[PDB]
Image (cartoon, coloured by chain):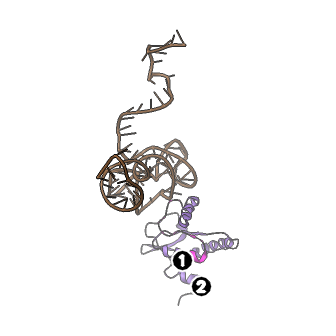
Chain colours: A purple, B brown
Amino acid sequence: YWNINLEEMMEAGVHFGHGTRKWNPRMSPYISAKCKGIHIINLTRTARFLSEACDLVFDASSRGKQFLIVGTKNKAADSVARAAIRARCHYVNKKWLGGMLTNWSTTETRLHKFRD
RNA sequence: AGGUGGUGCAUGGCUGUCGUCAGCUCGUGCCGUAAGGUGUUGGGUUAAGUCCCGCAACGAGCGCAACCCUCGUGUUUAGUUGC
């Protein structure tokens, strides 16, 4: 059991806090305290900044706009590969080649060469 | 008309030379105010930016290679002034 059964239940488990002394002083209003070296991120402001982030993507999916989910990191590669097949959107996974999001015209010629 | 008269530091054509060395560049996209740079760097590897990996680089063009000519094996076809 926890406090309440909502979205704040799963976020209060093992889904918060990361950086240890490698932080950027620009993200200062987005933290609570520094417990045992690790910087604990505030769940009160994340829930408000997740709401306005979920309001614009819902206002884009109703129109029929396309999304792109990038993730070349080893600890996030397997989760980025499954989430985009279910959503039918663009995704990068393996080695990141310089110029994929801007140079779509030069990289799609390689995709047509794969089909040739 | 004629000039093997001057000037190839006025020139065409052609050549040596470093060199067969292997480099020389471009499109798109990024970096910097900009001139430019990145790709043509790095780690190894080959005769060779040859190739692999890494990497805002991703691809491409000239060069390298190959395609052409002989030599080394055989096979098929045709045999004189060949055997």
Q: Amino acid at mark 1?
A: Arg
Q: Look at the image and give the residue range highlighted in magenta.
A: A84-99
Q: Residue at x 42, y 75 (%)?
A: A36
Q: Are marks 2 and 1 on the same chain?
A: yes
Q: Amino acid at mark 2?
A: Leu
Q: Which residue is mark 2?
A: A6
Q: Decide which of tag 2 and tag 1 comes sooner along the chain.
A: 2
Q: Position of residue B42 (x, y in %)?
A: 37, 55
Q: Is residue B48 above or below residue A78?
A: above
Residue A51 seen in render = yes
Mark number, residue A82? 1
Q: Residue at x 60, y 71 (%)?
A: A89
Q: Position of residue B28 (x, y in %)?
A: 58, 53
Q: Residues within 10 Å of mark 1 (few under 14, many from 20)?
A: few
**Which is more toward the observer, A44 or B29?**
B29
**Which is more toward the observer, A94 or B83?**
B83
Q: Residues within 10 Å of mark 2 (few under 14, many from 20)?
A: few
Distance from the alpha carbon under mark 2 to that under mark 1:
24 Å
State the count of labels: 2
